[PDB]
Amino acid sequence: PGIVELPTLEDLKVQEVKVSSSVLKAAAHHYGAQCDKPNKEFMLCRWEEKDPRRCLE
Amino acid sequence: DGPEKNYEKTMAILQIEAEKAELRLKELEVRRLMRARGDGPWYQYPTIDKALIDHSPKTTPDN
């Protein structure tokens, strides 16, 4: 009953970090505090917009 | 006593019975009517209150 709109694969070709899990967790404390501003903006969209497709940017 | 007492009193008896008779017929019709449609005070079968909903943010964004 309608379009299940999915974004094209073009916008999904984003630079993904290539580091093992321990690398993330080792610097986790020094990562969350100093990169909070985009983290909180993205996650606020996740809970507010409630739709994955809205927070692609 | 005079026939007037019986005459007027019987008219009151008729008036009471006529009003009661038409109300019972209205009772059957209304009860049938609002049982089906349901936009009436009685026959409102129980539902679940919206108060018992947790509106706080969950552990997953998609909710």
Image (tube, coloured by chain):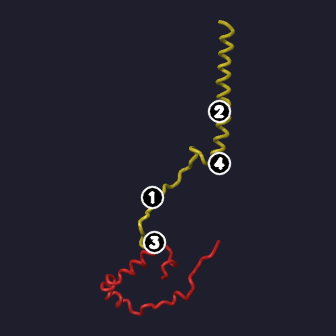
Chain colours: A red, B yellow
Q: Between residue A24 and residue B47, name the one nearer to us.
A: A24
The 10 Å Cα crowd at callout 1, few under 14, some 14 to 19, many 20 or more, is few
Residue at x 50%, y 77% (from the top left corner): A54
Alpha carbon distance from label 1 to label 2? 41 Å
Are callouts 2 and 4 both on one chain?
yes
**Residue B63's mark?**
none
Does B28 sit above or below residue B44? above
Label 3 – label 4 distance at C-alpha: 41 Å
Q: Nearer the viewer, mark 3 or mark 4?
A: 3
Image marks 2 and 3: residues in contact by CB distance under 8 Å: no
Judged by depth in the image, the label closer to the viewer, 3 or 1, is 3
Q: Earlier in the sequence, mark 2 or mark 4?
A: 2
To the question of a shared chain for discs 1 and 2, the answer is yes
Mark 4 neighbour density, 10 Å: few (under 14) some (14–19) many (20 or more)? few
Element type at marker 4? helix
Q: Quadrant of residue B1?
A: top right
Tag 2 residue: B23
Residue type at mark 2 is Leu
What's the CA distance linking mark 3 and mark 1? Answer: 22 Å
The residue where tag 1 is placed is B52
| Label 1 vs 2, first from the N-terminus | 2
State the residue at coordinates (43%, 63%). Answer: B54
Report which residue position mark 3 lands on. Answer: A48
Label 3 in the same subunit as label 1: no
Q: Chain of mark 1?
A: B
**Three-letter code for the amino acid on which mark 3 is drawn:** Glu
Task: Determine whether the residue tagged by mark 2 lies in a helix, strand or loop.
Answer: helix
Give the camera-side residue of B46 and A47: A47
Residue hosting label 4: B36
| Residue type highlighted by circle 4 | Ala
